[PDB]
Length: 78
Length: 229
Length: 50
Image (cartoon, rainbow over all chains, first blue to last red):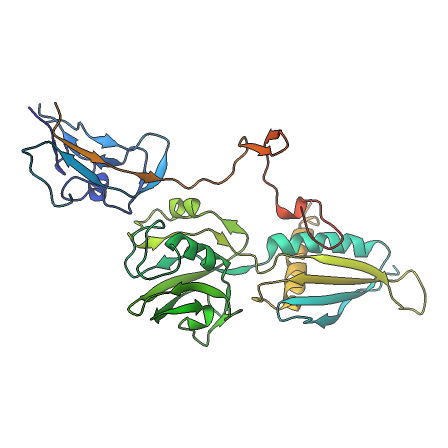
């Protein structure tokens, strides 16, 4: 089953989820640390196939560029 | 016990920020002894009034742009870090600055209050470069001694830091310059009595006499510990 | 095999810490290891530390 970006990540803590938007995407200007969720991508059978901050690094977030193949729907952020 | 106790015999505001001060009379070698310690204490120990907060009219991070302004946001933080102020009978306060139209900005533009003091109103703040341009920022001030990095501060606070609040490093010290000289001046109408002169440069936030007396009092605290054996 | 991508950038501000590599133009490379209370530094008769 194909992947999708969602805020409904399985079992992950609320605080990290708060950092994401309802699209499952961290906000621009956010401040993050190792393990903080950036992209809430998931896989069925559901699972947290998501992108998190590399361990041992902290930084501020400034960018979002979203790309899709032909025949794909967009999100509010994009 | 032949010691004559020195006193802060004279003070001089040679400049509105630079000052001179002298101590007399001083026993042999004590001028060097006190001079080194007082220099060391002043630089480290002095309590400072400094700014560490920026709330802005819509940018979300240090690296953000701004409409109709001459400089980037981050450069604004550097100017603010350079800016200094004195606060009366307070521990912290928030100040705001509002401007609109094409013009350069200075510390005087701030929404000053009588219980707050700006040491250099002429201090430079970033400029506006459009007729419809406008700035309306808010900044908070704190009392502290020494220096603190921004990252360490938030980790100690641990409460949520909302977007639009920007972090800068605290550099509290009201002063950073020390020169002191020992000279022979006439007391007891004889030689072997020492005269000490101190001079320093400041951001103007403190009275030099208070600085030495406050510093000396602080040193007395540590010195008193040696009686506690 | 993939039909949507997202790119995110992260900004890091870095000060100087012991072990950083420093170089002077005249081939004089070296690593710095200390940060001193400004009082400790040698200073001139004009009160200016290095």
